[PDB]
Amino acid sequence: IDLGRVIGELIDHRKLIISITSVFTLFAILYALLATPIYETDALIQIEQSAPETALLQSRMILGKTIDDLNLQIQIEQKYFPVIGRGLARLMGEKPGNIDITRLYLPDSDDISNNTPSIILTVKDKENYSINSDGIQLNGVVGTLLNEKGISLLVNEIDAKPGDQFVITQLPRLKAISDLLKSFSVADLGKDTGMLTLTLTGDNPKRISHILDSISQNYLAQNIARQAAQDAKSLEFLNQQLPGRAVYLQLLNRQQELNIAKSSAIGNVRIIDNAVTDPNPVRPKKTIIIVIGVVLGLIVSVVLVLFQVFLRRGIESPEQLEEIGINVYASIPISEWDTLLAVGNPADLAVEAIRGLRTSLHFAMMEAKNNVLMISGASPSAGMTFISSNLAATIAITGKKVLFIDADLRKGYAHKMFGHKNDKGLSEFLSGQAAAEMIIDKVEGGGFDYIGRGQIPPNPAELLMHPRFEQLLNWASQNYDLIIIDTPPILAVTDAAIIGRYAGTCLLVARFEKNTVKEIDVSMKRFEQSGVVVKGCILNGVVKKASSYYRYG
Amino acid sequence: IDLGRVIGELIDHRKLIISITSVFTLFAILYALLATPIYETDALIQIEQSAPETALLQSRMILGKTIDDLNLQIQIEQKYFPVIGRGLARLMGEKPGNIDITRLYLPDSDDISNNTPSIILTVKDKENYSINSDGIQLNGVVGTLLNEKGISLLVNEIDAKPGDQFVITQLPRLKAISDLLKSFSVADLGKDTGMLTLTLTGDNPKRISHILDSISQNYLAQNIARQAAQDAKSLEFLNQQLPRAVYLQLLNRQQELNIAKSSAIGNVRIIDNAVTDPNPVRPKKTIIIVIGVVLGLIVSVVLVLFQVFLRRGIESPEQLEEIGINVYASIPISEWDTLLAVGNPADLAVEAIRGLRTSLHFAMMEAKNNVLMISGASPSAGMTFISSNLAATIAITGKKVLFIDADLRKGYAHKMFGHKNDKGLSEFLSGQAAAEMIIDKVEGGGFDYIGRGQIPPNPAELLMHPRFEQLLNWASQNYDLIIIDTPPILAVTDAAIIGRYAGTCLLVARFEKNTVKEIDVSMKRFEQSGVVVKGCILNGVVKKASSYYRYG
């Protein structure tokens, strides 16, 4: 988990980490290139406070007058069936479609849920067009207003590209307020200065400048209207109260004072400069999400790789087994590769390591009480028969006579791999229905005598206790230089602990990443309980990255 | 309790955790889907302070005038017998019912507790209807008012759906003010700006906009009736004081006060009349559902950890080996009246018993005799299961096995192997039977079996009798193995009496039932009695924790 280990596993998993980081950056870049650009326009309003004005601008009288001025409750979008059709259309350089509807009146379904009757325009040419509400397509021409089925459309200046689809939505006036008010924004930047910087953000650049100018003009007009409206209510009741006659003349003097004031009462709000749209979109923020894509890919990659590190629990190196006090006799690397590897590809790495095992056993197998070696995998799929068979081959070619007993009576398949006469296997001998001679075979490849399990017997462990088995071993250890026995795991059945009574040397075979140290520890302790002293293990299937062996020649 | 152990038990208990988290999330879904929506409407009120205004709008003078204006003390609900009938009615798309009562006068029961006389409207059609107060159903039609039994009711524009029930409550004016006031709210957002955000929240969307509009109008008229009242008091005194140049000056002031009074532009303007946000603000969807998820998750965690800190039994042979107990086996639970070792010989729980046979055969050599005693740490430790199957799995090997069931209190081996209940073990110790008529032969396992026989009155006094050692000495010569079942030592002392003659003694501990304390005390009490317990035999270990697996 150290920095060195970190970089090691990173370069080892460089494919995964770069793949995930690159794919998230691909999502980021496609999103940055497909998200519609959003321009921002600004204006400067000057007054002589400004705290009421930042709230009166965003009031519904102001926005509500712009909406009715520009008909912004008539919403128009070019149709693109995919969620990214519009973005790719912009990327291709296609000029976006746009039309002007000066007067819209839907059939006004205006239901509780679907209060936005949605219609689609099919552009037929630059002059005529067709409108489908729910299938009923009404063909129409710009100029002439379409008044059918309670549906009133006055659409003019339709765009060029025909065949397009334009979704029209007569969303409610309150909605046409709320969206704008969401986009609209005000500030002061002087905390007392009359300057207000209105900002409106939107997609259609030319539209937002007009909308902001409309807001500014409405604000100008309404402030002119208010100061005058004070005097206007005064004037209204003066007009209502005119009938004493000298007082009538005094009221006429006040009337003439008030009347002109209304026309002349223009002030207190100022458009220092009308709205213009900044050509550079402010959103989507390029180079701010792509770096977020990079960092998101990096963080998720590390949080996944660390999770996988804390996932696996199998053996990782012989040092783990030697920590418990287990003499790992070999580390057989996994070979890329029906005949024996030790005779098919005699110079493979996995066979060089088995020769390295042969020498170490040859040293460790003298002083053993007899020349019978028992090899029991830690579990199925630990390769016990692979290692035992190749070891038998590599010891046969040396020149010693080897007998390879496959005492895995439960699911042993060595006879399925050496070529066999399935009759008269091992089990058929223990049952007493076969003699010691008709069971041995000759693997022509390895050159070592082979004894197969034969038929699966109903009672394996009961058979192995029969005293004929020790007779077999006593005879063979006199007629052979080495005897290798295959036995089932000790975590599953007790066959291994029965055969181990007669074996001089016993070894476990542990698959590299499959079997855990717990399985080896429990297996060795369970062998000891049964009076069988496990000599050591033979780590197997170690990946070539962690295997010390390499080609030499 | 470690992260690995945490996730292991979570996946093991994945059914429980997902079940409870899912059902609380379902409760959250149904609540969020049935909780009646509440809309809020907004209006904007300007002044040129606003600190008095935020408390004068909420005064009873203003609210109580809207109440009397819109008849808000006349409360109406569509009736739904369940607590969720209204919600599901909305779910089904059914348009909610509503009527209009322009004039309600109940009998005015107005008791101390039931100061809110409640009646129910039964909609008969679009024109007529019936009202039951306490059973007395009065039929009436819109238009004509029902004035009977002191009940003056004028309902018009009754809804369409007939047969419905409408609960009508003439709640007192103070309550009809207080509810509006708890829903009502004010703010300023400028701290000196005249801008006030009136906000009112209700369920009926169209109603609350009208309510807030009426509040605004009442407030506006009240502001007129303060300032126009100042000018009107001045003008009223002029009108009362008018009795010639001074008269013309007073007439000038008269018309000036006329215009100043009647103009009376309020310091307040309604910026924009109240409108209702179509999106309900409560119930807050996706804010309680996530709270439902986190609540289910936290309660699942706190319950699973509690159950973790609930069980005290053995959890693995390592716990026994820590104390210094040689766990000779771990027999897993078998799914499965004949012996398992002859019924289903390939069962995992029998493979483990063969594994025990081999370890005993090694560990039982050098023992002073071939007698094995197996005593469970408690009843329901499966002692007889293990001993019987072990005797079977040793019998098929070919050794002659004698199986003595010395559980003279509640032994039931004869109830399992098929029996001649006469002449059991007790009938031998009592001296009324000889050693030969007590022995049987289980045809299945193939081992000679000695039943306890009749429950004696004094078990322990019998077992001390010297005939028992005669039996064992004779058997150990005529049999290759002798297995003795004995009662738990924590309950009676028979086990420590038989153990004097047993070469090997083993305890059987159920996996999660028996604790480490029971095993430790059992071995200490065996030691005090001069019986050296060889080791334990963990029993009934669950397949999740056992290393055994099928092979073949």
Image (cartoon, coloured by chain):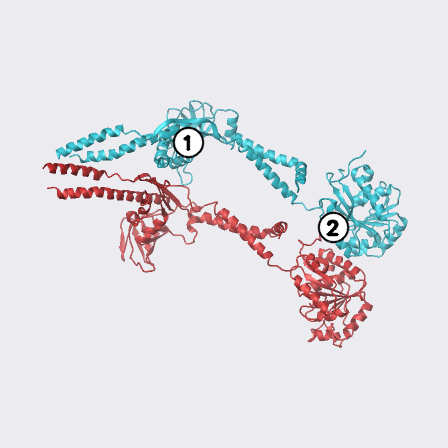
Chain colours: A cyan, B red
Q: Is residue B95 shown left or right of residue A360?
A: left
| Residue A486 is at least partly visible in this image | no
Image x and y of residue A27, in percent: 56, 33
Depth order, front residue of A347/A423:
A347
Query: Of all residues shown, which one is farthest toward the right?
Result: A479
Evaluate whether label 1 is on the same chain as label 2: yes
Spatial CA distance of label 1 from label 2 is: 72 Å
Question: Label 2 neighbourhood size at 10 Å, few (<14), some (14-19), many (20+)?
Answer: few
The chain identifier of the residue carrying mark 2 reads: A
Chain for numbered disc 1: A
Query: Can you give x and y, in whole percent of width and height, for residue B399 in the image?
Result: 81, 62
Q: Which mark is residue B196?
A: none
Q: Position of residue A66 (x, y in %)?
A: 36, 31
Determine crowd level at label 1: few under 14, some 14-19, many 20+ residues with C-alpha closer than 10 A.
Answer: many
- Determine whether, in the image, residue A75 is placed left or right of residue B338: left
- Residue A219 versus residue A124: which sits nearer the camera? A219
Dot 2 lies on which element? Answer: helix
Residue A199 numbered tag: 1
Q: Mark 1 or 2 closer to N-term?
A: 1
- In percent of width and height, residue A497 lies at 78, 54
Q: In the picture provided, is B279 more to the left or to the right than A495? A: left
Q: Is residue A241 above or below residue B100?
A: above
Which one is nearer the viewer's eye here, B255 or A425? B255
* Residue B371 appears in the rendering: yes
Q: Is residue A528 above or below residue A97?
A: below
> Identity of the amino acid at label 2?
Ile
- Contact between marks 1 and 2 (CB within 8 A): the answer is no
Q: Which mark is residue A324?
A: 2
Q: Within the image, what quadrant is residue B441 found in? A: bottom right
Label 1: element kind: strand
Foreground: B50 or A407?
B50
